[PDB]
Structure formats: structure tokens, C-alpha cells
Image (cartoon, rainbow, N blue to C red; front, side, top):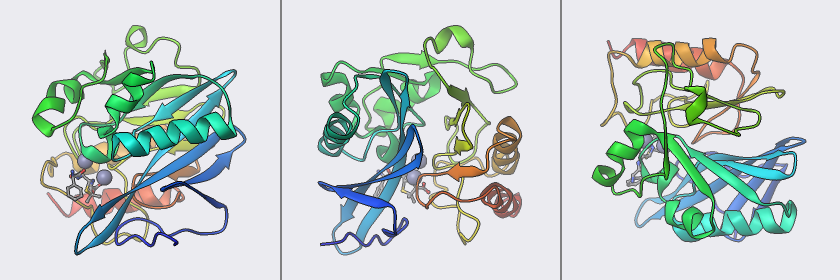
Length: 242
Ligand SMILES: CC1(C)S[C@H]([C@H](NC(=O)[C@H](N)c2ccccc2)C(=O)O)N[C@H]1C(=O)O
Ligand SMILES: [Zn+2]
Ligand SMILES: [Zn+2]
């Protein structure tokens, strides 16, 4: 019964299986969602996002791979937290991060992505978010484009895994989320570099670290949460691309 991914972390102590998904509490008001894409002849690919309780509402970072899996996330939220889901931020226009947009929209959840992610979305087979985030030259989100974001601190580190990749810190916690930009401290590969900026990747990884200097728990798309060594190692792998 247990899902054993070909890519992505395995289930460990602290993980809750719910439907086709896995959930792990990371802090009093933060959970990691994990969903799995089954590739025939290859196996499962795990992808991770976040769920944040901020006061009386829930904020989501990234969809699951599919609409149905994303609906399962909303069902888990209903059963375990039982608060309205106010908004989602999705971290670039690829299936692991935006495959479930229709499910969010059907539920009345407001969605936000980098303007560039919304521009790329149809070209990448994704439904665009309803609202566009824009960024200063230093990478920080323009505040008026991210209204009522609670503790979420949204940072565009520069082109890396993709040109549109964004990252999210959770103020008042030890957590920062690198999405697919960051790989864990023991990874041997940066994953899919097909859409990547190999010249600028290393600087973008370092910029993420410097934007969230305090965070000790680095959450990412395809590994369990790691130390800041994930940032250092990702940057060192990326140095080799130049
Ligand atoms: C885990 C991945 C190697 S695949 C994923 C993403 N790819 C997709 O979402 C594709 N739709 C896909 C196609 C076939 C099999 C799995 C995923 C990407 O290209 O960044 N993120 C990659 C990554 O984070 O390095
Ligand atoms: Zn991607
Ligand atoms: Zn990915």
C-alpha cells in the first residue's frame, strides 16, 4: 500500500497518508503536502508544497500534480484544519507546481503566481493564476501585488530551475521554501535542466539563501526538509554548469 517514489523522499516517521497523498506537520501552523505522479514503467514522482494556517484561514503554496490530487489537499484541509482556504501562491509554470489550478479555482480560492509564470502557463500546459505577482530588481515581491499574504514572504531569486521560479519564506517560523530550485544536500543532480538558466542558476540559489538568512528548515519540491546545506550544495552543483 505504501507509496515508494522513484524520485522524491520516502515515507518516514511523522508522515500521514491521506487518500493518495502524504502530509507532514513541520511547525504548529505549517504542513508539507506531498502528491505523486505515476509514470508507467518508471514509478512514482513525489512533489511537495506547503499549507499554512494564518489566524483563521489557510494559505497554500503549490498545487499537487493534478486537479483530483489538489481536491484531496482541500479535503484534508477541511478534515484536519477546518478553516477557509484564502489563497494559493504557485511557484512556477510546470505540472508539479500548477497542475491543479482548476481545482483551486473551482473552490473559490484566489490564486497568485509570478506574472511570468502566468505568461508561460498556457505554453506549459498550465492554467494561469488569477493574479500576477511582480518583483523589484532586488527580488522582493512588489507589496501591492501580494495583498493580505499574512506571514508569507515571496521572493524571486532570479532565473535558475526556470526563468519564472519563485520562493516563499514563512515569517515567524524557521521555514523557507525553495520549490524546484533547491535540491537537498545529498542530491547528485539538479533535476530537469531542460528549461533552466545554467549561467545564472548558482547566483539565484545563493540569492534565495541571502533572502531568507534566518531559515534553518529548507523545504523543497522533491526531498524531505533539509538544513541550509541544501542551499550551499545546490549552489555548488550549479557552479559546475557555468
Ligand atoms: C522532478 C523533476 C525532474 S520533473 C518536474 C517538472 N516536470 C514536470 O512537471 C513534467 N510535466 C513531467 C513530465 C514527465 C514526468 C514527470 C514530470 C520540470 O520539468 O521541472 N520538476 C523537476 C525538478 O524539480 O527537477
Ligand atoms: Zn519545473
Ligand atoms: Zn520539480
